[PDB]
């Protein structure tokens, strides 16, 4: 019943997380996904891998068909989506090499299809107004964090640990992301403004992927990879080692997801979609 | 003579504000309005009603044809537009059941047609740069407020009265709205950011409706309906509270139309159109 | 050698022209035809942002075509003028700002040369924009003002009481809004509380696209009024502008000469190198 979709960002243009069982060239009512979808098994848990930018990373963040990617995963029977998201750090405690299991975001994107529903032929009929107060699936967030612990990777929770317990590299138990449209990076002026707003990282791909996953009735969680500090503070090796440990986290997270019942969580996801219909 | 247009938001998809005299199924050079326009009278005052989202609430905020809506009302000869706007509160003193006669906004929408003019053939010829310092028609704002007074609804003015005078439910005499694109609600992160900017409410429909009304030379005023606290902070009571708010807003609207028709608006209307002409930057 | 493109904003819709040139671009047609000529020995190209009739609003300007057309003609530098409203007390109508920073609030504009759609160059370009302008070219605009005996105010070293108007502000940040409407008081105060200096509609993505084209770009903002945070309309932007046009013209002509008097070999190399190294599809 549980099937785990994986959307790989930078460093995961072609992951190979398991032996490929089948390759799926699909289309959706909202167009074609970034690439073909690879189906397989992690242990006894069915799993589907999909590169957000395509195999060659030729599709910029603003042009990614988030609808197609999410809906395609949904059509294949995924109940969860795990995503990676490379990012810049807006805080001194978040150091290149750290990961962040996001729990909040601020949206500054535009010109992207951010919803499956509407009044145009491009969309499913209805007006969907989805609650996003806490935009991720909390259970699945805690999976990612527990996965890191299982793989002996440091975890820092600012709510229960003081500064001295922050050993790098570490996974930050929470954090907020600002999603900019791209493709350019932020100016120093924009970086300081975001930092003053209390944001933790800056990224170009989280939104509307996270929003559409909830719309599709899926449990979604992102692991953000701190590649560098954003330009408020004036290499490839740290990122190479990062994807190795992110691979471990993803593989362990899939197993942890399959080790539990999700019947009521899946049911509540579906009901929230139906209850958010305004029409 | 005046003619008052009414753009009904949530809770006003099918208003029935008066006995329908005539219905207009029209189009504009900017496309189709949300729905048929219903014409009639409030007393001796001509009035036109249009649901922003259509009868069945099938049109989401981002896809509403604000241009067509404002232009269709203009074509029928409306001089004023009164709008309802459902919203979430960003401040402690603004509670569900309150109303807000907006005077300010902050815009965070995109991908919406927000001007009638441009250099493209599918827009009116010319470049219009409208001043928007005080984006509403002040006279018409004060009419909404006085209408609330006449209907025995509490009015609260933070600049004059102590917070000890804020008695719920009340019409807030001033307020700023942040307009987000939707269709999703804000995250807690976005809610606290907006609140820290000093914004009072969050809503998805105010802009560019208010902007386009000024571009059309019309007097525009919005009454926001506080349906809930935004996520910075039983549903059966929430629904019942909103229904009561709708009853109150309905009588405010009806009294407002009567108040408008009772006064002379020659100079205000003249100033409305002159403001349009003087913003034509291509006329130098 | 060097060649200077000049993108004129409001009131700039400069020399003895050699010829007028019509050009096309893989991203459409520029705002207008281009004026080719010389300031001294320095080749110079002049392009009005809104067209000769100012019929093109800021959100509909083809910044891609304008910047690329200047590139196609062999420009190494672009000087730009941008009319703006002030968000702070010390910046008054008649002042000028040699911008070093911005905050972007535009939408629906073509802001990159690269992408995966047919009407764009193939590739994913992620350009660093920490310091979005060419610093050398900024300091040239500022030095140009000194040569023409226009006051220069540096808020990093100078007193608020030592601010002599009209002056060129040696640094400043712009918020770029989409237009065509002006800001509300609410928006104006929010921008002010963010620490931004001016508000305008034309800087972005022009500045971004110039760096994509590997050109040294600098902007001089012309303060036409205070934004509505004080006690702004179309007619006001035009009137104040008149006296400011003359000073800006002097600065631009002087700046062109100053550019032509230095070697830009390594700067140009670095510009084109930054373009290549930002390609993340490779
Ligand atoms: N400091 C930043 N600001 C915005 N995006 C960033 C960073 C750092 C990494 N990314 C992500 O990686 C790609 C561009 O480098 C894009 O996919 C982007 O999401
Ligand atoms: N807390 C909020 N944030 C943003 N919009 C809100 C609310 C509450 C109500 N609305 C308005 O009503 C519709 C969404 O329910 C939309 O039409 C919207 O304008
Ligand atoms: N206070 C302001 N806010 C926004 N834009 C302003 C100003 C003042 C000038 N401009 C510039 O003038 C043009 C539109 O009038 C546009 O080119 C615009 O950049």
Image (cartoon, coloured by chain):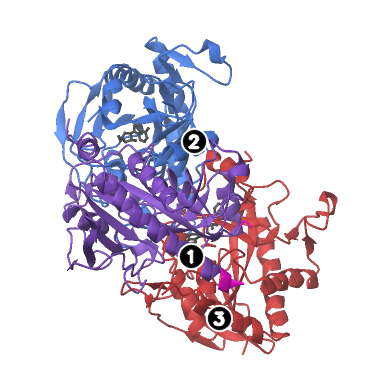
Chain colours: A red, B purple, C blue
Q: Is residue C41 left or right of residue A171?
A: left
Q: Quadrant of ligand 3?
A: top left
Tell if the residue under mark 1 belongs to the same chain as the one under mark 2.
no
> From the viewer's perspective, is residue A163 above or below residue A131?
above
Label 1 resides on the chain identified as: B
Q: Residues within 10 Å of mark 1 (few under 14, many from 20)?
A: few
Q: Which mark is residue C189?
A: 2
Q: What's the residue at 40%, 14% (across, down)?
A: C166
* C-beta proximity under 8 Å, tags 1 and 2: no
| Front position in the image: C105 or B73 | B73
Q: Quadrant of the N terminus of chain C?
A: top left
Q: Quadrant of residue C76?
A: top left
Label 2 resides on the chain identified as: C
Q: Gap between marks 3 and 2, in whole Å?
A: 42 Å
For label 3, the residue is A271
| Front position in the image: B19 or C179 | B19
Magenta residue check for A258: no
Q: Which mark is residue B244?
A: 1
Q: Is residue A255 left or right of residue C188?
A: right
x%, y% of residue C264? 42, 29
x%, y% of residue A218? 56, 77
The magenta span reads B232-237
Q: Secondary structure at mark 1?
A: helix
Q: Gap between marks 1 and 2, in whole Å?
A: 35 Å
Q: Residues within 10 Å of mark 3 (few under 14, many from 20)?
A: few
């Amino acid at each position: 019943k549980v099937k785990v979709g994986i959307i790989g960002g930078s460093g995961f243009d072609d992951p190979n997380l398991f032996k490929k069982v089948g390759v799926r060239q699909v289309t959706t009512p909202f167009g074609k996904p970034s690439d073909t979808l690879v189906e397989g098994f992690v242990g006894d848990v069915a799993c589907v891998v999909l590169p957000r930018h395509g195999k060659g990373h030729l599709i910029p963040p603003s042009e990614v068909n988030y609808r197609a990617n999410v809906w395609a995963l949904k059509d294949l029977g995924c109940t969860h989506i795990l995503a990676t998201n490379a990012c810049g750090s807006l805080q001194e405690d978040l150091v290149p090499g750290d990961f962040v299991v996001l729990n909040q975001f601020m949206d500054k994107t535009w010109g992207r299809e951010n919803t499956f529903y509407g009044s145009k032929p491009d969309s499913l009929k209805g007006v969907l107004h989805m609650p996003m107060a806490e935009p991720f699936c909390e259970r699945t967030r805690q999976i990612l964090i527990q996965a890191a612990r299982n793989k002996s990777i440091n975890v820092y929770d600012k709510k229960t640990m003081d500064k001295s317990a922050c050993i790098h590299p570490c996974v930050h138990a929470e954090g907020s992301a600002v999603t900019i449209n791209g493709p350019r990076f932020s100016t120093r002026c924009e970086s300081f403004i975001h930092k003053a707003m209390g944001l933790d990282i800056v990224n170009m791909t989280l939104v509307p992927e996270v929003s559409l996953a909830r719309e599709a009735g899926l449990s979604y969680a992102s692991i953000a990879i701190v590649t560098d500090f954003d330009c408020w503070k004036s290499v490839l090796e740290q990122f190479r080692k990062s994807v190795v440990h992110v691979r471990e986290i993803l593989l362990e997270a899939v197993a942890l997801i399959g080790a539990e019942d999700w019947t009521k969580t899946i049911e509540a996801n579906k009901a929230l979609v139906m209850s958010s219909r305004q029409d």
